[PDB]
Structure formats: structure tokens, C-alpha cells
Image: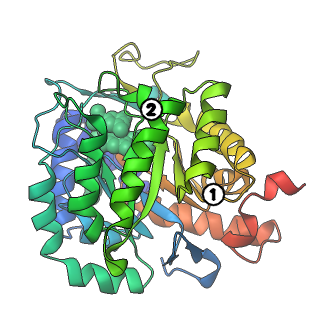
Amino acid sequence: GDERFYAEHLMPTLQGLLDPESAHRLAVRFTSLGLLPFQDSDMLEVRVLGHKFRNPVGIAAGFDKHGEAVDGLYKMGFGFVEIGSVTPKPQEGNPRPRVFRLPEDQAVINRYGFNSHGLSVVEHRLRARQQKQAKLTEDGLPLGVNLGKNKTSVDAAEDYAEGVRVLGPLADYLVVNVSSPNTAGLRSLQGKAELRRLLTKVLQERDGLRRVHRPAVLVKIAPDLTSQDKEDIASVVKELGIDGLIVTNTTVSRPAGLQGALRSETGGLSGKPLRDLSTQTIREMYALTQGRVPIIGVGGVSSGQDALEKIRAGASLVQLYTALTFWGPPVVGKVKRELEALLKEQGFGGVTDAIGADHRR
Ligand SMILES: Cc1cc2nc3c(=O)[nH]c(=O)nc-3n(C[C@H](O)[C@H](O)[C@H](O)COP(=O)(O)O)c2cc1C
Ligand SMILES: C/C(O)=C(\C#N)C(=O)Nc1ccc(-c2ccccc2)cc1
Ligand SMILES: O=C(O)c1cc(=O)[nH]c(=O)[nH]1
């Protein structure tokens, strides 16, 4: 496993031979079979959400939408895996092309639209390795399951409720994904009244599961929220005792300076141009929740510094996806190695010590 080789030769050649969706599909395939190219120190261990995480670097939702490559992803060095988004019924998503690379920006735009094998398929896939996962979790490698809703559903809350009932028993944590920019009307569920109603139902359904099968519940939010939106989300989270937040999904904004020819494609923008917008959203949400609500920080993480900035801003854990598509699997070890070195350099005894450090200076 060599960073230079992947960054300079393998990935650019892959990007030059296949379209983005094809590259994604082949990657899931390769990862699922364990055809892949760092020893986690105690400094990187985090205890949150009722679990030990051997390192704080996870794979973000969207890469493994259907739970096909979980074990290969742990082998890649991720401290936790999130699969999904999964919808109740199977659905195809948007017509192709629906994924676009912006190499000049180290960015991606996608409009997949919740292409999903559906709950039943994912349920059986996870059941086939349920005890293996139980041991992985105990060993500090938890599993998250990200829930979406069907395009033609009349009752959004019931979609998420069904997700809780079916995949909740198989997950260490669940994500109520109300932040995809690619499903019409979905982001409106972030509004105060809609969110409270939705999350009340979700939490009731979760509380009804047997104790060993009872996951933490997190809400994944957009980077495009107004100050009022963020205030309201913070209020509802505290009112209902939501276990955590995932911050953030992709942006519908197109920051000044984007160079990629494909910058004006419809969809969610990810990668470097999203990075600081996400970090600032983490920072705001941490403050609004008084540091009492665990945050998983996501968006434009490609290095140790990127990870630590989100951690200092208030994230207990981080995730990446887009960086993997540019630098390949070696980015995981790179992020962890750089993060460890930076923690030492900045006087932190571990990740835990650095969580929210910016707010205390
Ligand atoms: C191709 C693609 C598909 C994605 N699909 C999902 C999804 O199904 N559910 C979800 O919550 N986030 C999804 N995401 C968003 C990521 O989980 C993450 O929040 C975002 O991409 C920012 O992280 P990054 O810059 O490291 O990619 C997707 C992102 C991309 C790149
Ligand atoms: C949307 C998406 O996943 C991509 C694009 N564009 C993409 O390139 N993904 C990807 C992710 C991982 C890998 C990879 C490369 C080597 C070994 C295992 C996996 C290759 C490609
Ligand atoms: O299109 C999707 O499936 C999707 C894309 C994205 O960026 N975020 C998300 O939650 N879903």
C-alpha cells in the first residue's frame, strides 16, 4: 500500500478508463472481496454513542449503499462503517449519468437519488454476518445504518419507522437522513415541526426494540441550513434526547472558485470545496448543543489536519468518502497517521482530549 502509487498512477488511470459510477461499482466489488493494498494506537480510541471506536475515521454513507462491502471496509482501516442510505422498498434512483468528478476541485457532484436494494435485501445481507459484526463491534469496530425514504412514499415518517424496525436490530447506530439534496421535499423534514414529529416516531420505534438490539439514533443534516434551521434542530435534538448528529451531507451550493467543467451539474457537491462549510456547521451545532450531543463530522476530510479541525470544532468522530475516490485506500492510513502526529504535536493525550478544544480556548 503506497500513497504515491495510488494518487499518481492507479486512481488517475482508473478515472481515465471508467465513468464515475462504473468506478464506484467496481470499487464496491473489489472491496467486498477484500482485494485491497497502519497499527491503531490507543490515542485514536474514542468512546461515544455507547460504543468503543478503535479509531475515529469512518467511511461515510453512500459508498456502500447496500451493505455489500462492510468487512472489506474494516480491512481498509476504517474505525467504523456506515452503510446506506437504504430505502424501505427497492428503487432505481435517478437516470444515468448521475455522478460527476471535478478533478480540478478535488470534488464530486452526485444525484443518485437513493438507488437502493431496499430494506429486505439489506436485512438478509446483514443477518448473514450478524454475529461476526457483534464481535467486530465489541472489538471497537461499530456499524452504522443510514435510513432514507422512497421517492413515491406518501408518509415519510413511516418510511423511517420501517427502517428502524427492520435494520435497527442489526445496527450500532441508525441515521435519519433528512439531508439528501436529491429527493424532492426531503430537506423540508429538517424544519422544526416536521423534524419533531418524525424523530418522536423514530425514537418510539427504536425504544420498542429489545435492549441488545437497540441502536443509537442520529440525524444527518445539510451544510446549507439557515441560522434559524440550526437553532431549531438543536432545540428538537435536546428536547427529544436524540443521541447525536451527522454533520454534514453534501451541499447544493456552488462555492465561488470551482474550476471543474461539470460544476453546474445538478446534485450534491462533496470533497474539498465542502470542507470548511462542514467544519463551521459542526462548530455551530456543537455550541448550540453545549457540547452534550455527539457529532460525527463529515465533508472534505482528506488529511490528518482536516480530521483534527473537525474534532477541535466539536466532532467526536469523522467520516470521509470523496477523498477515497481521488487517493484510493491509502488515504485512510494517511489520515490516521497524520492525525496521531498532530495530536502529539498539539499536546493532546488522545482524540478525546481534542474534541471541542477550539471552544475552550
Ligand atoms: C456518490 C455519493 C453518494 C452519497 N450517498 C449518500 C447517501 O446515500 N446517504 C447519505 O447520508 N449521504 C450520502 N453521501 C454524502 C456523504 O455521506 C457525505 O456526507 C458527503 O459526501 C461529504 O463527505 P465527503 O466530502 O468526504 O465525501 C453521498 C456522497 C457521495 C459522494
Ligand atoms: C463515486 C465513487 O465511489 C468514485 C468516483 N467517481 C470512485 O472512484 N470510487 C472509488 C472508491 C474506491 C476505490 C478503490 C481503489 C482501490 C482499491 C479499492 C477501492 C476506487 C474508486
Ligand atoms: O443521491 C443520493 O442518493 C444522495 C446523495 C448525497 O449526496 N447525499 C445523500 O444523502 N443521498
Q: Is residue 6 visible?
A: yes
> Which three-letter amino acid code belongs to the residue tagged 1?
Val
**Alpha carbon distance from label 1 to label 2:** 20 Å
Q: Nearer the viewer, residue 104 or 182?
A: 182
Q: Position of residue 97 (x, y in %)?
A: 18, 24
Query: The N terminus appears in which quarter of the rendering?
Result: bottom left
25 to 78, vertically: above or below: above
- Tell me if mark 2 has few (under 14), some (14-19) or many (20+) residues whose alpha carbon lies within 10 angstroms of its own: few
Q: Position of residue 135 (x, y in %)?
A: 32, 87
Label 2: which secondary element: helix
Query: The C terminus appears in which quarter of the rendering?
Result: bottom right
Q: Is residue 271 left or right of residue 17?
A: right
Residue drawn at (83%, 71%) of the image: 347
Mark 1 or 2, nearer chain start: 2
Residue drawn at (28%, 50%) of the image: 161
Tell me the tag on residue 247. none
Q: Which residue is mark 1?
A: 293
Residue drawn at (20%, 37%) of the image: 21
Label 1: which secondary element: loop
Q: Is residue 60 visible?
A: no
Which image quarter: residue 280?
A: top right
Seen as rendered, the residue at the extreme right is 361
Q: Is residue 285 left or right of residue 188?
A: right
> Which three-letter amino acid code belongs to the residue tagged 2?
Glu
Q: Position of residue 19 (x, y in %)?
A: 19, 32
185 to 157, vertically: above or below: above
Tell me the tag on residue 194. 2
Q: Position of residue 263 (x, y in %)?
A: 41, 17
Q: Nearer the viewer, residue 203 or 98?
A: 203
Q: Is residue 27 left or right of residue 77?
A: left
Quick check: which quadrant has ligand 1?
top left
